[PDB]
Image 1 (cartoon, rainbow, N blue to C red):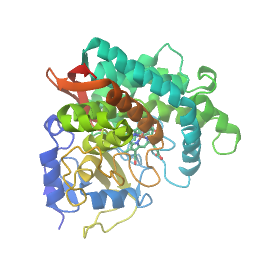
Image 2 (tube, helix red, strand yellow):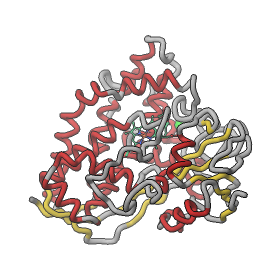
Image 3 (cartoon, rainbow, N blue to C red):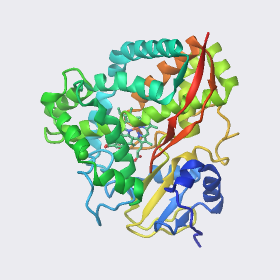
Image 4 (tube, protein in one colour):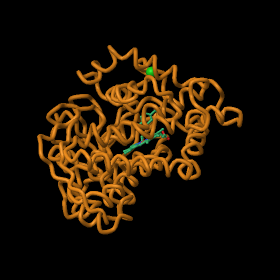
Length: 393
Ligand code: HEM
Ligand SMILES: CC(C)c1ccc(C(=O)O)cc1
Ligand SMILES: [Cl-]
């Protein structure tokens, strides 16, 4: 009753161009079986949203990668928030929601905005840049480690470690096994930086440790939550900002609209998150048989959610393949949905908003003037290199 497909969503051909295969996945039915990896797949908005919003049945505590923690050893101790179910999830979630809350945003906004304005001014001084290395990477590297209160030495481990983490959500293909078998120095750095004495007061990390006396988390849990922020807080925004620049380069009319009204910057970033979905896919594991779109899924089965496909599903979105910075984007699943919905989403939106605002106010044109090169990751979508020429306003 469930169609079986041989599409490999973790192959280089898929990463190079996933949209045709994503349509095939959506149009085959509400639930498919992926013979390549023996998992169920859901690619339509309705089913992705339903799965995300039933975390008891489609749980996270058995891993959100292909591996089932009840069958295999986790490559690292499980995340206490990403890879936990309620009620164990609830208190760490509350701590991270309070660390990365509105008030903390007000405390970091001026530095983030100044850094974004300064970056755009510098890049306009460069004229010809790599929008990845020189912008999408450089800006978050210039503000997020400070906001975490990391020392200067070793911050070079953050992006490699993140790539590993996201590769490790994939199947045991070359990307995953490559990341995990040689990984140890990055793990050593991250774990060391998670300890209270190495995290400067006033930063996100030290605030996590500071919540360890409120009764929400214990001292032994705080390092692992800092590890969550060091895993998730940099690379996702790098590919999101890269996505937004790529969209504005490919849709010059939308750049002109954004320049004319820079207050669209936040929505312009949000629509980029919808349009490219930096985080493409995540798994759940069924804790019971669950009829989903008329299809039966067994106990203990992995279910692959195609977030990007849900964000391009024509059943839900008008002109899904257009980048529209005045689109009503609310309801997209690029940040997830439900109890695990991105707890860092305000940081991501702040970085994206202030950077797109800086471009809107300072840049007249973004023209691609070189080969665009894609970065391959089992979970992340984004570019390796995006050479552009920036014309000043
Ligand atoms: C463009 C930027 C970002 C994107 C697209 C993104 C995407 C996502 C998605 C799809 C989820 C849901 C995972 C799931 O349901 O299993 C998630 C959760 C999470 N994100 Fe982000 N994220 C971004 C930025 C950030 C930042 C900047 C931080 C921290 C500083 C962060 C930290 C987290 C954490 C800790 C979770 C787990 C929350 C939970 O399990 O309750 N993310 N993110
Ligand atoms: C959703 C993604 C950005 C993410 C990755 C790792 C963790 C963690 O280590 O807790 C959380 C979220
Ligand atoms: Cl680790």
